[PDB]
Amino acid sequence: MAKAAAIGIDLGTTYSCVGVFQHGKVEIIANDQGNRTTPSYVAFTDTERLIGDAAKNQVALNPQNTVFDAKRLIGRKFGDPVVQSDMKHWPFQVINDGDKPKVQVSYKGETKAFYPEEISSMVLTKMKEIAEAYLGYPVTNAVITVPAYFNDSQRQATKDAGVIAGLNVLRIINEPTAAAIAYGLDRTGKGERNVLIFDLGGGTFDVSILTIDDGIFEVKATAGDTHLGGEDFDNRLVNHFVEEFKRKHKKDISQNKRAVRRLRTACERAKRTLSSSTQASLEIDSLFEGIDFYTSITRARFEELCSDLFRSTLEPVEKALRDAKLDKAQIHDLVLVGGSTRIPKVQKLLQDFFNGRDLNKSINPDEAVAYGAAVQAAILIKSTR
Ligand SMILES: Nc1ncnc2c1nc(Cl)n2[C@@H]1O[C@H](CO)[C@@H](O)[C@H]1O
Image 1 (cartoon, rainbow, N blue to C red):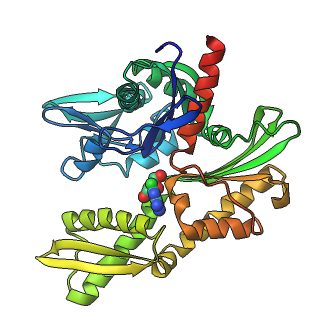
Image 2 (tube, protein in one colour; image 1 turned 30 degrees about the vertical axis):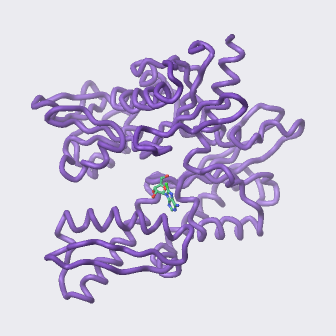
Image 3 (cartoon, protein in one colour; image 1 turned 180 degrees about the vertical axis):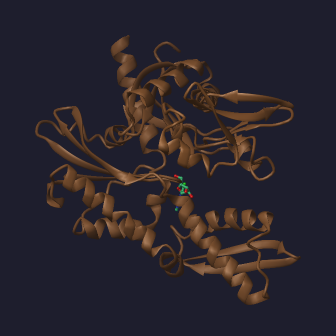
């Protein structure tokens, strides 16, 4: 029953996803709002603790007490230059507890501080409750994914987040390995198979090269940009619409925090529409000083606005190929991961770089990692008996 059941969790920087392998198929489980992915956000309010969509929806009104990006801190020391650099950009407080970072917030009128693993355990608890509501019984066995470049300390702190959340962690697997499992790339029989995973998410970009020699996975190279993702494309749209508002009304909206946020969320939505239509419309009632902002943007203009960012994704691809000592024609499979890989220009650039090659993209790219983890969790729980 419950003891023979196992889930796969993609614990992401900005979004998390949970899957279950049953009756010969993977089911990516929808949360209580019907979304197949949940924001990795935890809000602390005057009355409650919010996790996911409800936490992300009130981020504007409560920025000091809304924690996100815990994955950027997990397993790291406070003195780490990555932690020191990131802290300058977060609206929440990060404190030092014996060279270990803690996030400090106000909760039910009291000052409370949490380790990154305690923050990640609240996200993991939500993913566990989403699976339990779908299954009708508690599931406790889980496979949790991490980036391929995570060291031993980051992997141990992720397993600890799993323990705090009440999960029996069957294994901590690499995100590009879960993605290759999702496509069944470890079941092509004998002979070394070279796979490139192109992972473009909300806030990070990762390129991984794996060799799969008879079921055995080996990471040959990792490359990328930890501060490149979908949110940079939203911000380029925001800047365009702020300048268009200035041309139409001779008014600068950039300082009005509410106007910029409403425009940002509308830009994110318009960006997603541009992945399946050649134009998208913005319909913002009373954006600034009672002025409605009813406009549109073509996919061509959007591609121009983000042109330099899209092209920059090819430098880590070349870098990973040189570190792996492989030429382009030596790569057997190209796998797309992350919601931003749905952008047609991104796909065209990667396909032209690999000389017109087909891309593995039939599995929802923001769900492929959870899909593979769910597959591995079923195999692992079956062997445990
Ligand atoms: N259809 C889409 N076209 C473009 N970007 C998309 C799309 N879907 C998602 Cl999710 N994203 C973005 O992926 C990230 C989450 O993985 C977010 O930045 C989201 O906007």
